[PDB]
Amino acid sequence: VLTCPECKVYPPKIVERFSEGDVVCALCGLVLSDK
Amino acid sequence: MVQQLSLFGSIGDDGYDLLISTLTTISGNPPLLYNSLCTVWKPNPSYDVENVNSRNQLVEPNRIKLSKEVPFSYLIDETMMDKPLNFRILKSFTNDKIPLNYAMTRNILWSLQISDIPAAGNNRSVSMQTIAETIILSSAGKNSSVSSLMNGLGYVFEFQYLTIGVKFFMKHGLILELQKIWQIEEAGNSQITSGGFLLKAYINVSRGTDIDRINYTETALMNLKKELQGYIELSVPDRQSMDSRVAHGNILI
Amino acid sequence: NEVFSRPEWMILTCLPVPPPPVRPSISFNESQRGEDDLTFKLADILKANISLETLE
Amino acid sequence: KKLMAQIFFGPTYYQRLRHMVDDKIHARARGPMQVLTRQPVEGRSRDGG
Image 1 (cartoon, each protein chain N blue to C red):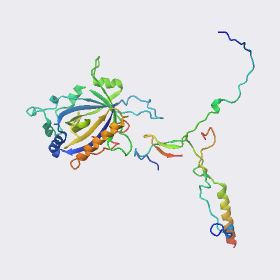
Image 2: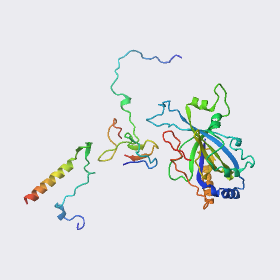
Image 3: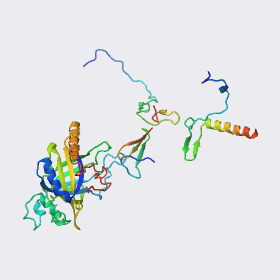
Image 4: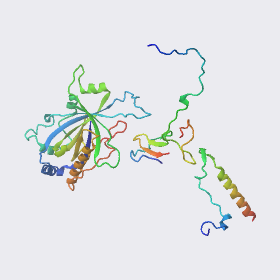
């Protein structure tokens, strides 16, 4: 399970940026996991 | 556009009088009565705003606030002209009923204002919020009215409320407000801040880039909070409560 | 050397098994796991060892 | 103006070869890694290093 520690919204909304190797919350723009 | 740095709190009316005296002991100024009337408007759901860039989230829909001052002759009933117009009248404003009803406000229909959710992060000691403001001076035409104007822009009415309270001006541009809020509907008037006063201490900064000024403002606000220790607890409100975007609905009151 | 390089150790008795990072499995789908060559060789080693043990 | 020196001038035959700059241009700040060595992948169409 992977959740944003600032929006605190369930279920979390998440978009994976494959071309940058990142996982990004779609609301605050925060970067969750890299590489 | 300002960066408003704010701290919040609340008190029960029992200590109200006492509180007032203490403030005058600190500021050296007497309280000044004031009132206001705010109307909230939201984008029309009949119109499909496909222009919201869903794949990029360039922008999200938001709510507009229109404020105006209303003379006390609309707020004083036939039992109250004998008393002078000062702060003590607030002691009689404990009932959910109020002279200003729905029909008068409908007959009325300024300052236009938009805001954003406060800044993220847990290393912020005061609520920092960004505000964009403009002023409407007058109008003309065949349908000159606030309602027609906001429908021309693309917004519709959502609700409204009435604030009555007192103001204290301290040094360094610090403003302290004691408020009572009455929501108004055709069904009637209900006091949300029932049996108490809402306390808000805030400062305004004109330019967000200047950081020396912001540090000074935070220092003044924390010093004020540390002065009132033991009487009233001033706290940073919830960041998710001061969010006014249409997608999610809640209202700090 | 007495501490690091005794000659008795040049003959194997126990074989260390490397973690899966050294031999990563490539998973096309949920039930499609293509395993590395190293794990196949290690499986054959263990199969032969158990066969020799059960004949012993 | 006029040019001091004259110029050799005339038609010729030319062919447009198979190499375009649009098929050779590549840049990378960050991106996917490798399963085993965990180093930037190989390949322009797979935005590698």
